Image (tube, rainbow, N blue to C red):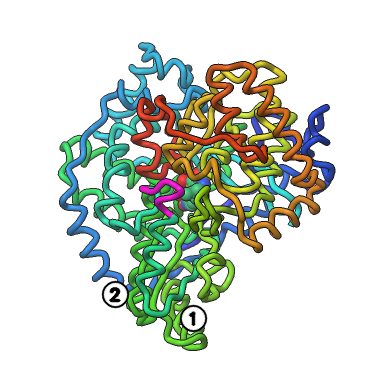
């Protein structure tokens, strides 16, 4: 069937859109080439519509149904609970889009009677009606990149009340079931370092290792009614409250399977028969579906000891090599299977034999050295997009502070330490806004984070090593430095110089500022300080940062 049918009505915005990098007095200090940097808008929504709209066909064999039976058996060991309206309301982002029924996210958060009462009506409706399609808004995402122009991605989401209801029915399922079903293959269970460890450990268990990333062209659009019903049969495997079963069944039929699409103007834009990107089950659905199709495809392609690491639609396999051109033969059969399963590639998958050159989740393992000289593996990425977005955030205040999220996730990296930390802490200093908590997203979930906690956060996630990394890899150094020349970013010599200022200004304030100055910037000096554990690190509750993924899932921790 066709992933989308369109009526001709446009995908429209709520307000005016900037595609051109906003410029303030702080811009040139970071990036000179403003022409590179752009944001996607509703303007290109037609281009995307062209791309995401295709016919799907599926060829399900025994490998598929065999993998499915295993997955279901594991799933049948999960007991999951209903969240109450109260609990579900507290998982709603303060800034989450308001309801069509006369209330917003903050009404839902402090549990106002208008909000709670409607949500009950929605729930009652879900239990009693299992046929009537649920309305969705379709929108074009505004996202910031560097010239490589990508069209805007699309986002499809149900009304606020339905979203609270999703949490009640499924939050606990989508949080706990993926790890039970897929074990070590589930990626959102890992911090950046734990992901690096699982990869390296897994790479090191192959006699002759081969790995590849599989890029599915428009994953959401490949996902069929079958897949979406297949994944519900997995959900229903759990021990569930009877109202959870009904609600999960109703939500699958009325929402997840598909339904009518409506623009911000209230115009009928058509109909979706594929995965919605703005529902609770998106990340978990994509994860289960990708792991199902991919595990089966390795039985097809007859891959030797195939190990997977799945995060939604992002797939990486590591297996035994059958020789360089037998692998090339192996992957084409894999792709053939994946393609039969309704999941063809965007780019053909190339086999790698250098772990440090496998790109999965936009990232790759690299290597550097700690204080002792000891080789330490860490996760890194191409800083192009991070710095393009940091440029936008230099001039605009936005819902998601990508720089803060990037510093957290990529603290051990050259570019994050030298540029991201140096630029943004300087800005917080200048405004004396070091103490203001900032929203940022990790695995799709929203978090309020105070920048002064960064040292404590970084020690816990990465270890004291991250404050001491040096002698980075030559290909890593080359990539950063080349990205810099491309974006017109100052050379790392200037950043080293700026950082000495920032450190000094931070040390002078004392308190947590000195702590930030001490650990985050010890790299800046030649006469270096000896770094010891911080007391506060034990007191932070990070248990929940890397359990599950919730892209488009309206989650706030
Ligand atoms: C271990 C990690 C460092 C690897 C890179 N990384 N980084 C982040 C960051 C959060 C904040 C700054 S970077 C991050 O939020 C993600 C995420 N990756 C994917 C990938 C693939 C998907 N696929 S989907 C849309 O669910 O079908 C979803 C996500 S996410 O949950 O939105 C977050 C990520 O993969």
- Position of residue 285 measured from the top left corner of the image (x, y, whole percent): 37, 51
What number is the disc on residue 63?
2
Q: Nearer the viewer, residue 258 or 469?
A: 469
159 up-or-down from 42: above or below: above
Q: Identify the residue shown where x is 62% and y is 40%.
A: 523
- Position of residue 2 measured from the top left corner of the image (x, y, whole percent): 50, 61
Q: Which of marks 1 and 2 is in front?
A: 1
Q: Which of 131 and 146 is in front in this view?
A: 146
Part of the protein shown in magenta: 189-195
Q: Nearer the viewer, residue 304 or 61?
A: 304
Residue 166 appearing in the image: no
Assess whether residue 132 is covered by the magenta stretch. Answer: no
87 up-or-down from 238: above or below: above
Q: Identify the residue shown where x is 38% and y is 27%.
A: 540
Q: Does the residue labelled 1 lie within 8 Å of ligand 1?
A: no
State the image quarter where residue 426 is shown: top right
Q: Name the residue under label 1.
A: 332
Q: How many labels does the image show?
A: 2
Cβ–Cβ below 8 Å for labels 1 and 2?
no
Assess whether residue 192 is covered by the magenta stretch. Answer: yes
Secondary structure state at the residue bearing disc 1: helix
């Amino acid at each position: 069937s066709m992933s989308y049918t369109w009526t001709g009505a446009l995908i429209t915005p709520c307000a005016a859109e900037e595609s051109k990098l906003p410029i303030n007095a702080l811009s040139n200090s970071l990036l000179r080439h403003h022409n590179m940097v752009y944001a996607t808008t509703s303007r290109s929504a037609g281009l995307r519509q062209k791309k995401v709209t295709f016919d799907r066909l599926q060829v399900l064999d025994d490998h598929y149904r065999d993998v499915l039976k295993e997955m279901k058996a594991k799933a049948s060991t999960v007991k999951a609970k209903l969240l109450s309206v109260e609990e579900a309301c507290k998982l709603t982002p303060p800034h989450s889009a308001k309801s069509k029924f006369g209330y917003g996210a903050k009404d839902v958060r402090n549990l106002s009677s208008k909000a709670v009462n409607h949500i009950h009506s929605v729930w009652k409706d879900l239990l009693e009606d299992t046929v009537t399609p649920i309305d969705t808004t379709i929108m074009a995402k505004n996202e910031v990149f560097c010239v490589q122009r990508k069209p805007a991605r699309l986002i499809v989401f149900p009304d606020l009340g339905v979203r609270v209801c999703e949490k009640m029915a499924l939050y606990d399922v989508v949080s706990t079931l993926p790890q039970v079903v897929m074990g070590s293959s589930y990626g959102f269970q890992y911090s950046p370092g734990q992901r690096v460890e699982f990869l390296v450990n897994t790479w090191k268990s192959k006699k002759n290792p081969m790995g590849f990333s599989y890029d599915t062209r428009c994953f959401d659009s490949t996902v069929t009614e079958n897949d979406i019903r297949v994944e519900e049969s997995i959900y229903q495997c759990c021990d569930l409250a009877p109202e959870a079963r009904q609600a999960i069944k109703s939500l699958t039929e009325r929402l997840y399977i598909g339904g009518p699409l409506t623009n911000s103007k209230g115009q009928n834009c058509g109909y979706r028969r594929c995965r919605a990107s703005g529902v609770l089950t998106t990340s978990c659905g994509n994860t289960l579906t990708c792991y199902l199709k991919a595990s089966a495809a390795c039985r097809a392609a007859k891959l030797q000891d195939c190990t997977m690491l799945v995060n939604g639609d992002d797939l990486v396999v590591i297996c035994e090599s059958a020789g360089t051109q037998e692998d090339a033969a192996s992957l084409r059969v894999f792709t053939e299977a994946m393609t039969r399963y309704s999941a063809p590639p965007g780019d053909p998958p190339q086999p790698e034999y250098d772990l440090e050159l496998i790109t999965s989740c936009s990232s790759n393992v690299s290597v550097a050295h700690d204080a002792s000289g000891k080789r330490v593996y860490y996760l890194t990425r191409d800083p192009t997009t991070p710095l393009a977005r940091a440029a936008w955030e230099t001039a605009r205040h936005t819902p998601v502070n990508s720089w803060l999220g990037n510093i957290i996730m990529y603290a051990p990296t050259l570019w994050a330490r030298m540029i991201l930390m140096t630029h943004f802490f300087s800005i917080l200093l200048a405004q004396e806004q070091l103490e203001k908590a900032l929203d940022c997203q990790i695995y799709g979930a929203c978090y309020s984070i105070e920048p002064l906690d960064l040292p404590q956060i970084i020690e816990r996630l990465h270890g004291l090593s991250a404050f001491s990394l040096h002698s980075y890899s030559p290909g890593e150094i080359n990539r950063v430095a080349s990205c810099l020349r491309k974006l017109g970013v100052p050379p790392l010599r200037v950043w080293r110089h700026r950082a000495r200022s920032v450190r000094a200004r931070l040390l002078s304030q004392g308190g947590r500022a000195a702590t930030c100055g001490k650990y985050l910037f010890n790299w800046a000096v030649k006469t270096k300080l000896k770094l010891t554990p911080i007391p506060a690190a034990s007191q932070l509750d990070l248990s929940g940062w890397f359990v599950a993924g919730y892209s488009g899932g309206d989650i706030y921790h």
